[PDB]
Image 1 (cartoon, rainbow, N blue to C red):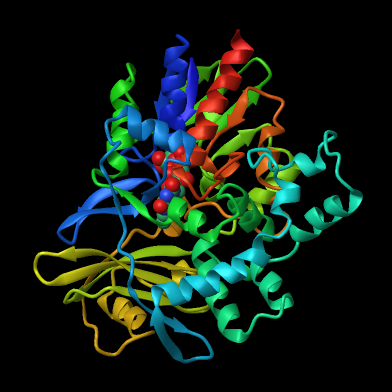
Image 2 (image 1 turned 120 degrees about the horizontal axis):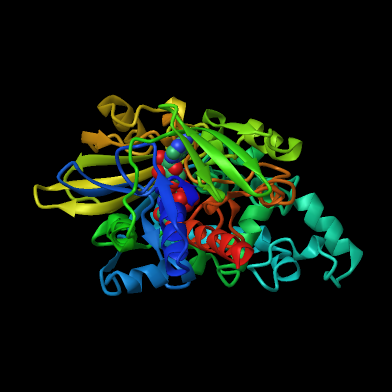
Length: 440
Ligand SMILES: Cc1cc2nc3c(=O)[nH]c(=O)nc-3n(C[C@H](O)[C@H](O)[C@H](O)COP(=O)(O)OP(=O)(O)OC[C@H]3O[C@@H](n4cnc5c(N)ncnc54)[C@H](O)[C@@H]3O)c2cc1C
């Protein structure tokens, strides 16, 4: 009787949790596929992750699923020791990957500042604003101020030179997958807290280990455990929600009565659903503003075998580009992240060549691909990232729902929020527990 909207990782893991508890459920998915913003598909001659790629054993929820579904040894590190190139004052500088990582590491020290005072338990991000907070008032003041400051201004104010500013600009265009200047620095500080406050750990967690058999090995694994068939091609159009239950109406007009609704539709796509009663004003403000998630991910194929890393600041088409696969026909597939989905066509060879031309004039693009999640009606965003003010008055507001409508998804997680499948698996599971505990 529990209706789960969406067959991404949050909805799939919530269904499995309800199944463990003996609670009847149904998953309604708009697309003709499961996985959501995780999507492994053959393109350009090999399986490519069009969304979600990297994992780590320090991500508890993701790692448990890797172990459950047989993928313990089926991980491979992305290429390292690349020849690095970065754009700073309109010019290309060359160096080793170590040289670049050394500059980023120094900048991260200032970027993380305060994380040890804010996040002693990095899974209690709002402890500073709780009644259990016992530190000095200046820590709470700085915490609130940091929600209104972007991560680049922290580096500027610390006196780093233009080269380092341009490097962190590029870095956070990728990390905020959007304009980093509108973002909340508290997001970066919590990533530090979850990464033992070390840049190398943060990159090991978010940008190193890939699944040989893809995210699909995990999402197909969860779906394979479910005893109730997923209803594909069944978009939800309306959710009526009250203290005792809910009523869901699909696009086709079908009415489904529910004891509770677990809604995993991300903010970028919530406007497709009519909520009755209307969602609270503070939650609607977040939906209207969005998340800071307007960027895009590309896969580019070039001739030859090239160990390449490139960084470029806003407003570049792509801000971080790295070699990922060396193919058997003397080509290299590279991944790229850019701040602005509308400034690049992910499937245009000319735009992909323009990306590579940001750093070199001697590399030739032969193929390119990607899926523009921001222009996907059922997503409307890449991974969720925080605008100024959204660390303290954003993601946590979706819990302030008195009715039997529950919001679950990576974007509302306490831990690796938005950026990681770990957050979807966390919040899908704990939202199922909210439903279970209420019924018990
Ligand atoms: C480009 C990109 C790269 C990423 N890389 C990584 C990475 O390297 N590592 C990592 O850990 N994470 C990564 N992620 C993040 C990861 O993909 C997400 O955190 C996670 O997949 C989100 O899961 P979810 O279940 O919360 O939401 P979703 O996956 O968005 O699931 C929501 C589901 O609801 C469906 N839906 C939407 N509207 C409706 C409707 N009206 N009715 C019915 N169904 C509907 C959608 O089709 C979708 O299937 C990346 C994300 C992106 C966008």
